[PDB]
Structure formats: C-alpha cells, structure tokens
Amino acid sequence: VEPARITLTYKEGAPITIIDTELLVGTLTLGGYKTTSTSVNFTDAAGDPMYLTFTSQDGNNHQFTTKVIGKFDISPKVNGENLVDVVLATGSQDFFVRSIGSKGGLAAGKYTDAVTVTVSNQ
Amino acid sequence: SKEYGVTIGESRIIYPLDAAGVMVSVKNTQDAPVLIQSRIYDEPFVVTPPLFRLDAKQQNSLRIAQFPRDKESLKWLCVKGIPPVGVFVQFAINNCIKLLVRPNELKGTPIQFAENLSWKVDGKLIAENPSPFYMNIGELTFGGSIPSHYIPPKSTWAFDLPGARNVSWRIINDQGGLDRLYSKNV
C-alpha cells in the first residue's frame, strides 16, 4: 500500500527593495505526489482569485500581490483559479512566487502571508 | 529554506459501505509540532480526532467512520498540518486523498473493468465508464498526453482534446499503484 507523502520546501528569494514587478519573492518545491496542475491549490485569507496577497504588519494594511507559476509557463490554482492544465513533473515540481505589484500603492517593513497548499491526490 | 510535510499512510481509502470504520495513519514529517486538522469533503463521515496536536516526527491514527448501493461514491479526506521590504510566509500542507465508498453488492474491483472504458471524440475526448467503479486514471495519452481525471461510475467524463486516434491509459489500482496499460483505437 502506497502512502501519500506530500512535501514542500520554500526557498527565500533576493531581498526586496522599494516595488519591481516580476520579482522572484521565493521558490517553492512541491514533492511526493503520485497528479496535474489543477490538482494543486494555493489559498490564503485574502482569497483573491489567482493571487497570494502579502500584507504589512504595521497596522497600515499595505498590500502587494504575487502570482505562482512554473514551467512553457504553467500554474497551479491560486485561490481556486489558474492564472497562466498539465501533468506535473515526476517526483517534484518547482513553483515560483513572483511579485505583481500593489493595487493600492507601500511602506518599507515586514509583510506576511499564511498560505495553505491543497493537493488532491490522483 | 524551510521544509513542510504531511504523510497519510495510504493514497486512497476503500470504505466498505456501512462498515463501522477504518483507521489511517498520519505523520508529521516536519521538525516542528503542528495541529493536524482533518476534514471530509463531497466530490456523514466522522474523522476522529478532527483536530489534534502532532509533535515533530510523530505519527498517529485517525478513525474514519460512516449512499447508492449500485455504485461507488467518492469523498475526499483532507489532512492539513497547521502551525499551532521583508517577506515572511508560512505554509500549511493540505493533503487530500480519495475516500471511495464501496457497496458490498459490487462484483469485482476496478482493475477487472479498466479495459472496458470506451472512447469517442466530440466537440473533447470523452471516456465512457460502464462499471460501477470510479476509474481513477493515472496516465492518459491521445494521439501520442492529457491531464487525467477519474471517470465516475456508470458515467462519462470529457477531457479537452490537446489526427492520430490512439488512446492509452492506466488506472490507479486499489493499492495506489499504476495498473496495466490499455490501448484502443478511437
């Protein structure tokens, strides 16, 4: 009987300075799945379809959005929707978190997100 | 770099209809404790415990306890490991596997009927599953690759076409392994 092991490794990208678009915020490696791109869904509290939202911690509620993409460019669902369906590579798949920008226009400081990665095996 | 992980002892559960329950192991493969939050989703079932602390490297058991009788039903068991310009992101893996509710009235197993998928192209590559089982395709190619999906029992499923007409597929057997390759001309 095969176990369903799911693993995720997150690697930080370059420091961000005030923002440039298409900035590589960080890289994700999803592993262990037996599985297509629409079987993976990255969700967060903002729940903005196609984007993860990062919010400042200073009480000022500054925010910027990011997209999650891999490689031909592909994408898992983010908050229930694809941005840019394929079979994921064997063993593991790299996804890149890339800055879009801020619809509200950003103080320097610390920004956060809590992201759930849902993998529907098979 | 930061690593996350949630392991479920099986990649699918075959739940005999009306059975008292089944047990399944879950392991926190991360080096920090998490809360393990378990939920069952539609495509009536109790998961005990639905939330509990699982320390670093520790494994515990979940109990899953309970529909048409002429065919399988599909549910999803999701097991999530929750942590109980500078960018700080935290992740939580939500590991979901198929909960296949299987009536005892049913003769055989999916592998007995994997060959019986019939195919046609309209609009979309359409599969037809006349068996009372979910045909959980794990590999599918047409005209030499299609993102697969299960075919529901006594039903059809339409895949987007990606003039060659071969279709080759493998289902995933009850044990989580890839079954034999079947091939038909469409």
Image (cartoon, coloured by chain):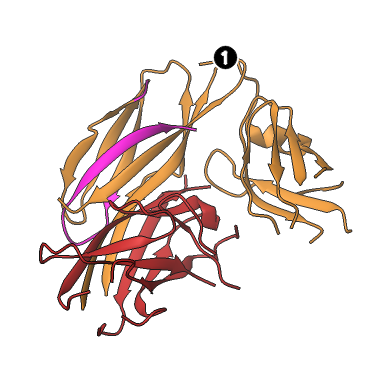
Chain colours: A red, B orange
Residue A91 pos. (x, y %): 49, 65
Marked residue chain, label 1: B
Residue B117 pos. (x, y %): 76, 37
Q: Quadrant of the N terminus of chain B?
A: bottom left
Residue A99 pos. (x, y %): 37, 74
Residue B143 shows in this picture: yes
Characterize the local packing of mark 1: few (<14), some (14-19) or many (20 or more) Cα atoms within 10 angstroms. Answer: some
- Camera-side residue: B68 or A22? A22
Please state if A46 lies on the left or on the right of B99 as rendered. Answer: left
Give the residue number, with chain letter if any, for mark 1.
B69
Indicate the quadrant where residue B60 lies: top left
Q: Residue B76 in magenta?
A: no
Q: Is residue B42 above or below residue B78?
A: above
Indicate the quadrant where residue A111 lies: bottom left
Q: Residue B39 in magenta?
A: yes
Residue at image x 18%, y 40%? B52
Give the residues in magenta.
B27-45
Please state if B152 lies on the left or on the right of B144 as rendered. Answer: left
Indicate the quadrant where residue A24 lies: bottom left
Q: Is residue A34 above or below residue B12?
A: below
Element at label 1: loop
